[PDB]
Image: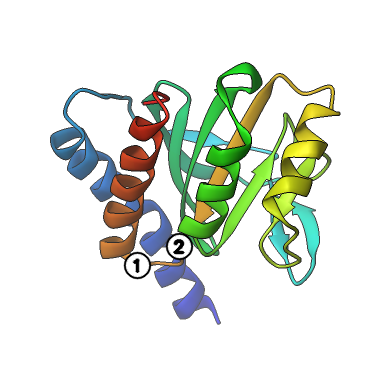
Amino acid sequence: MLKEVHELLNRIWGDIFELREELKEELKGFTVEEVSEVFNAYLYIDGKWEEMKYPHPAFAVKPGGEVGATPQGFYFVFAFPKEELSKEFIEDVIRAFEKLFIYGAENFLEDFYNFEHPISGDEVWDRIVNSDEEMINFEVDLGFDKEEVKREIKRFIELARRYNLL
């Protein structure tokens, strides 16, 4: 257990330090900040949101972005003001990414879309319109696939550009 767990922890942190430098170089035009430690975030494990009282690594990508890793693997998330969004963007993002979550201020509490129990894009938009949430987060989870983090961030940025979001 210990040898395997030590290796996994070195992978989580080593991969994010590496990815930060890579995206700093590659995402020109975006301000890419340093890796920091995030405590008390929740993750969706085996059908339930569970709090991580331990830290996990993440770095900001402005505006409104974060890239990081948890024991599940890499993720990125971008937050946009509700008034900038539209039903069509919501529909497009749902079709564009596999392990997608769309949520308000708290992922464990204000879930608009969870890919594990998917609903229609129209229903997602209705939930957003009828909510008390100003900032809407779009998170894509990727396991430990470095090629996919790079490609999916690129696809996300390109989709966002179409809607004048990034």
Query: Looking at the image, which is closer to me, 55 or 105?
Result: 105
Residue drawn 55% across the image and 29% down it:
79
The crowding category of the residue bearing disc 2, from other C-alpha atoms within 10 Å (few below 14, some 14 to 19, many at least 20), is: many
Residue 59 appears left or right of 158? right
- Between the residue at mark 2 and the residue at mark 1, the CA separation in whole angstroms equals 6 Å
Q: Is residue 35 visible?
A: no
Q: In which quarter of the image is residue 14?
A: bottom left
Residue drawn 45% across the image and 78% down it:
3
Residue 138 appears left or right of 143? right
Residue drawn 55% across the image and 25% down it:
80
Residue behind mark 1: 145
What amino acid does circle 1 point to? Asp
Which quadrant is the C terminus positioned in? Answer: top left
Q: What element carries label 2?
A: loop
Q: How many marks?
A: 2
- Residue 108 at what x, y percent from top left? 79, 45
The crowding category of the residue bearing disc 1, from other C-alpha atoms within 10 Å (few below 14, some 14 to 19, many at least 20), is: few
Q: Quadrant of residue 110?
A: top right
The reply to whether discs 2 and 1 touch (Cβ–Cβ < 8 Å) is: yes
Residue drawn 51% across the image and 52% down it:
140
**Which label sits on residue 26?**
none
- Compared to 117, does 122 lie above or below? above
Residue behind mark 2: 142
What amino acid does circle 2 point to? Leu
- Residue 160 at what x, y percent from top left? 40, 34
